[PDB]
Amino acid sequence: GFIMEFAENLVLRLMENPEERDRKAREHIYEMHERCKKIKEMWALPIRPYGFWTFERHNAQLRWDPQISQVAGRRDPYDDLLEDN
Amino acid sequence: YFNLSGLILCPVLGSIILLFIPNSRIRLIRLIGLCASLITFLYSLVLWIQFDSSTAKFQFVESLRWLPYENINFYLGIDGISLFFVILTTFLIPICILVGWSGMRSYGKEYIIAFLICEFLMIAVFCMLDLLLFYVFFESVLIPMFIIIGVWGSRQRKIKAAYQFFLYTLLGSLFMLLAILLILFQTGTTDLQILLTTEFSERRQIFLWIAFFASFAVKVPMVPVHIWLPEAHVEAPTAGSVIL
């Protein structure tokens, strides 16, 4: 053929779907705003959590001392006296 | 299918390739620099043809995650306003290489490297939609133009021109950065589309607008600070004086 009859549909192939572009734009806005709200919530967390000491890793002694309160140097004076019988 | 990312990558490839070759073969350096600039220019013109002027939403968007939360990321994209600036900045660079073509043996490969880095960085500024990262690239041009002005400039006052140029883009730039941080903490994201659809406090917009204008009243030669352009522009090379 001639030049323009091919350059026309060439440019038309080069250009994209606008419906896809609009859908992607509204989508991206939706999830970006949702993620923005999520990050805003995340930044509100205090440095020290409400539980803190309640956490099992932050006790480390309520389940260690009971198995140590029997060794010498930690016993209540009234433990060795009546342990004989 | 030519996207926006290839246009950004072309100067990067031209610069990386140029560093591989030595400095003895000067003809190769100038030839490859001019070829890279010209193919970038052609790519920019190609992007013009496939530009939908009917829709209001942005054209080609390439998103590369920056923070682990995808809170802020490289959001490239052109519109009716940013397209012609991209075309102009792609068009001016080959002219910059061509003006000093005779003296290339005196400048060296640092000259073309600096100019191609400038082309890459200036393209990245105009066609991006992330407010914070646009600030990063917005004064990222400090280093390459500082090198261009200082290394090949005036006789002995080249030092003062570099300092005035570098000093005028510090206080206002960081005073803008403070507003950038307030916007980021207030809303949550720096995405341009998200920031457009936000209710800012009536008293808040005054401070943020003043902070933005303070860093733009130095780039645009406003009344208080415009004396840098004459002195730092006479004390500048001809190819550095044509993009400044």
Image (spheres, coloured by chain):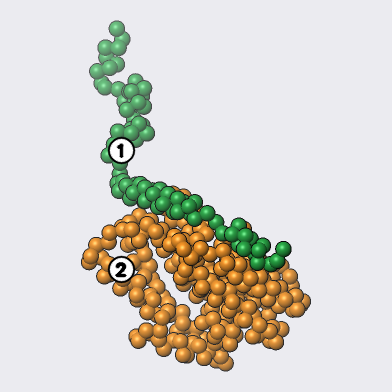
The residue under label 1 is: A52
Which quadrant of the structure image shows residue B87? bottom right
Q: Is residue B213 above or below residue B134?
A: below
Name the foreground residue: B155 vs B206: B206
The image position of residue B14, as x and y in percent, is: 66, 69
Q: Is residue B167 above or below residue A80?
A: below
Tell me which chain appears green. A
Name the foreground residue: B181 vs B187: B187
Q: Are marks 1 and 2 in contact (CB under 8 Å)?
A: no
Mark 1, secondary structure of its residue: helix
Which quadrant of the structure image shows residue B115? bottom right
Name the foreground residue: B232 vs A78: B232
Q: Is residue A72 above or below residue A9?
A: above
* B137 left or right, relative to B225: right
Q: Chain of mark 1?
A: A
Q: Chain of mark 2?
A: B
Chain B, chosen colour in render? orange
The image position of residue A21, as x and y in percent, is: 48, 54
On residue B208, which mark appears? 2
Residue under disc 1 on the same chain as residue under disc 2: no
Residue drawn at (74%, 78%) of the image: B26
Q: Is residue B117 visible?
A: no
Q: Residue furthest left?
A: B203
Which mark is nearer the camera, 1 or 2?
2
Query: What amino acid is labelled 2 in the image?
Result: Leu
Q: Dot 1 surroundings within 10 Å: few (below 14), some, or many (20 or more)?
A: few
Mark 2, secondary structure of its residue: helix
Residue drawn at (34%, 20%) of the image: A70
Q: Is residue B215 visible?
A: yes
